[PDB]
Image (spheres, coloured by chain):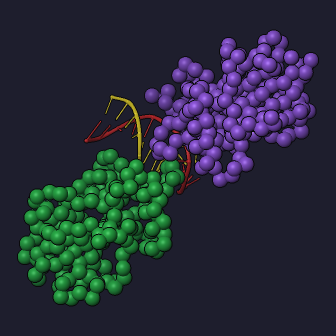
Chain colours: A purple, B green, C red, D yellow
Amino acid sequence: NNFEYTLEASKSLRGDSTMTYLNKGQFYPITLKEVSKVRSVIMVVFAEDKSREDQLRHWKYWHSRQHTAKQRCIDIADYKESFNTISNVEEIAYNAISFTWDINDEAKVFISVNCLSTDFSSQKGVKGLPLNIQIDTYNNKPVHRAYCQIKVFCDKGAERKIRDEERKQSKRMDITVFKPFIDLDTQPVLFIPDVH
Amino acid sequence: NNFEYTLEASKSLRQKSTMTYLNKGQFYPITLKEVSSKVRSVIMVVFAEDKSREDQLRHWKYWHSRQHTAKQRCIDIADYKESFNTISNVEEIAYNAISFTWDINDEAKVFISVNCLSTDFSSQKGVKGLPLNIQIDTYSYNNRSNKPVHRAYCQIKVFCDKGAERKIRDEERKQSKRKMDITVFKPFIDLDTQPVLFIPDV
DNA sequence: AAAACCGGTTTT
DNA sequence: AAAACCGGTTTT
């Protein structure tokens, strides 16, 4: 039971960990593949600290400053070409989306992150928290687990960050493969859980 | 009856609308003198672009709400002995207003710090800061009429840390390639209008 | 102390 | 769509 998840967006160059830059509200194509209908859950969580006290503290802070209470941390596009490969789509939480797909057919979804990396601090001129796109694939534990470290920028910030990086070194590659996670028996924190 | 107020700090050196840059919490020397009798002057900090009392209080209340200390004042005067020599009856009538009495025949010097940033009025990130005004109303004892015989202001912007000096460098290096340190207060004709006061006291 | 970093914003 | 502007922050 081995899997390979793929995110297609602008990727950084060279940093020793995986890094991917995304735009707030912009949809990105995620690929699901294994080497029997299985259920996978795509989530957005923090990377540096996985303590439930601190993560929810951030989420609660972010949600309070949001203009819409209905606004979700993560969204999936209601595109028919996505709904062809998957179904039984359920939003179990504001930062979690669950759906069922088949192994024999490669699954494609479109995901957008609606929170900025800087929306967790009131400070001005600061870097901002790194985020993780975690996909759990579930027979009450996942057989496979992977994550993808990202940073979300306002407007078209993701493309600008690439330019600045390219001019740093001054003085295929658009594909990001999810990094597998060994720990399976730990539960990820969920912000405002639904569908009990 | 003519007056002259003086602020010694970093001067804009730009459009030639004089503008002066200050650091939050840093004291600056203000000079008060009359040219060709104890008089009372009030030094205040108010907004420049919009003077509606509803909006000014809206800004101040926003700033005050984000402050770590409720006792924190918009404007402060240094308890310096060389300052208390030229003035007296120092009273802080408001969080953004300080009143004191001085004599004409002796030049008055005080030390003032602004404890609010120009960007502390918006939650937004990466935007310009609001312009502020240092307004000095001078109420005469025999003239009374609850109105200043003279009025002047000084348009300023307050920067974090040593930001005021940095803004000068960027400005100095800009006009270098392409395109006195003393700032004199600009007099104001309208005297019978009342300045906005945040949390009035006394 | 001056200069570079950071990213939302604004300009072009 | 690619760079400049802005100012708090960090680095040197």
- Measured from the top left, where is residue B5 in percent x and y? 21, 71
Q: Which residue is depicted at the point 47% across and 39% down?
A: A126
In the displayed structure, does residue B170 sit left or right of residue A140?
A: left
Residue B14 seen: no
Image height of B47 relative to C4, above or below = below
In the displayed structure, does residue B173 sit left or right of residue A55?
A: left
Residue B199 seen: yes
Q: Which residue is depicted at the point 30% across and 47% down?
A: B162
Which quadrant does the N terminus of chain A fall into? top right
Q: Residue A162 lies in what quarter of the image?
A: top right
In the displayed structure, does residue A91 sit left or right of residue A165?
A: right
- Nearest the viewer among B192 and B66 is B66
- Measured from the top left, where is residue B150 in percent x and y? 24, 81
- Nearest the viewer among B29 and A192 is A192
- Measured from the top left, where is residue B179 in percent x and y? 37, 57
- Measured from the top left, where is residue B26 in percent x and y? 26, 52
How many numbered markers are drawn?
Answer: 0
Q: Which residue is depicted at the point 34% across and 85% down?
A: B192
Q: Residue A182 lies in what quarter of the image?
A: top right
- Nearest the viewer among A61 and C7 is A61
